[PDB]
Image 1 (cartoon, rainbow, N blue to C red):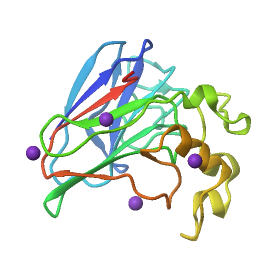
Image 2 (image 1 turned 180 degrees about the vertical axis):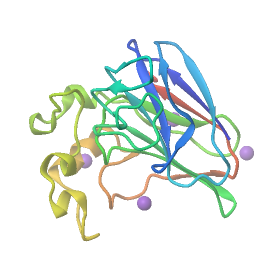
Image 3 (image 1 turned 135 degrees about the vertical axis):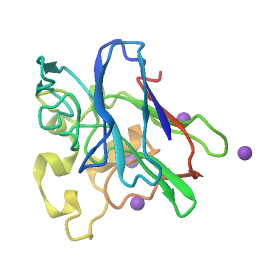
Image 4 (image 1 turned 90 degrees about the vertical axis):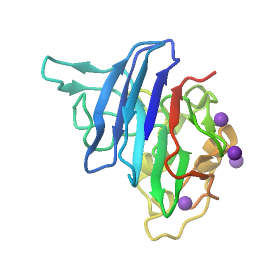
Length: 206
Ligand SMILES: [K+]
Ligand SMILES: [K+]
Ligand SMILES: [K+]
Ligand SMILES: [K+]
């Protein structure tokens, strides 16, 4: 499966792609404003994520830091990113279909559209100004809008028991972005696509 990753932001981002225990494709690349990067993701990939990182510095070797979504200081992510991170999430070729969503469960850093480039399902989008409207207690000094689990580390925000309800904080995310997961047990906003669909992730789509 191909994913075209497109940075429409006025600022540089460092795209990242991982399934948590490994890179997808090269795992990360710089995208200047306007640039497109196409990756190939193995069929059957389960629990993959794509995200943007902001304000990154890398050396020679591909090692450094980012202020949002840093993945163990690698340019080329092999692991998931440090919140806050708006997340494009996908599982491919799961009993005949693909499943995509956007999640704010790990907070929000960059607005995003995640859409098929092939037939037979809708895209999803979270492109509201969550960072600008972020509740004060969730603002990350580093940049972005943290989720409540990240900030407060409670069973209720993190849904540790698998028992949790929506919260004042999750409802903020949901209000701004109805079509993205706002907490672990949110009413799913997952879209079913044909197996082996292809996709475009667009940062700052509007
Ligand atoms: K169709
Ligand atoms: K869309
Ligand atoms: K709400
Ligand atoms: K779910």
